[PDB]
Amino acid sequence: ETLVRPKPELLKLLKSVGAQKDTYTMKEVLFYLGQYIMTKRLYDEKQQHIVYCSNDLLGDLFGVPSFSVKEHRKIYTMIYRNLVV
Amino acid sequence: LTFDQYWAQLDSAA
Ligand SMILES: *N(C)CC(=O)NCc1cccc(CNC(=O)CN(*)C)c1
């Protein structure tokens, strides 16, 4: 599996929920990001595919006030904007 | 679904 490299801001985000390395598989990046969103309770209690990130670092990194977990292609685009090319 | 079940669907695309 291909190893990818987070930029400094994303890296600090992943290391806040136990991540220990400088490079990751994409399944690992998606693991730590999910643990972040769910630990901080950013998902809507009632409509659990929708994430509110307006007052969070994640909103600054992704450039949105919210997104939907159904939009797979859009989540991948937003993650790849935050990886070293 | 639960947040966990929607989020699992992304693992698939990886
Ligand atoms: N791709 C990394 C995601 C995936 O499908 N595997 C990681 C995984 C598996 C099982 C459980 C979790 C964490 N889930 C929770 O903490 C709560 N949701 C039920 C992650």
Image (spheres, rainbow, N blue to C red):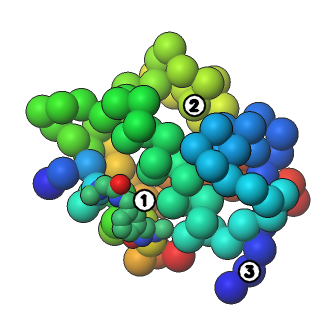
Left or right of B3 in this view: A61: right
* Cβ atoms under marks 3 and 1 closer than 8 Å: no
Q: For mark 3, what is the residue?
A: A2
Answer yes or no: are tags 3 and 1 on the same subunit. yes
Q: Nearer the viewer, mark 3 or mark 1?
A: 3
Q: What residue is rendered at 53% in x and 59% in y?
A: A30
Horizontal and vertical percent position of residue A72: 42, 59
Left or right of A80 in this view: A40: left
Front residue of this view, candidates A64 and B5: B5
Please, is residue A78 above or below residue A30 in the view?
above
* Secondary-structure class at tag 1: helix
Left or right of A81 in this view: A76: left
- The subunit carrying tag 1 is A
* Secondary-structure class at tag 3: loop
Front residue of this view, candidates A38 and A5: A38
Q: For mark 2, what is the residue?
A: A58
The residue carrying mark 3 has its beta carbon less than 8 Å from ligand 1 = no
Q: For mark 1, what is the residue?
A: A72
Q: What residue is rendered at 83% in x and 39% in y?
A: A8
Nearer the N terminus, badge 2 or badge 1?
A: 2
* Cβ atoms under marks 2 and 3 closer than 8 Å: no
Horizontal and vertical percent position of residue A37: 44, 39
- The subunit carrying tag 3 is A
In whole angstroms, how far apart are the C-alphas of marks 2 and 1? 17 Å
Horizontal and vertical percent position of residue B6: 27, 58
Visible in this render: residue A77?
no
Q: What residue is rendered at 46% in x and 48% in y?
A: A35
Nearer the N terminus, badge 2 or badge 3?
A: 3
Label 3 is placed on what type of residue?
Thr
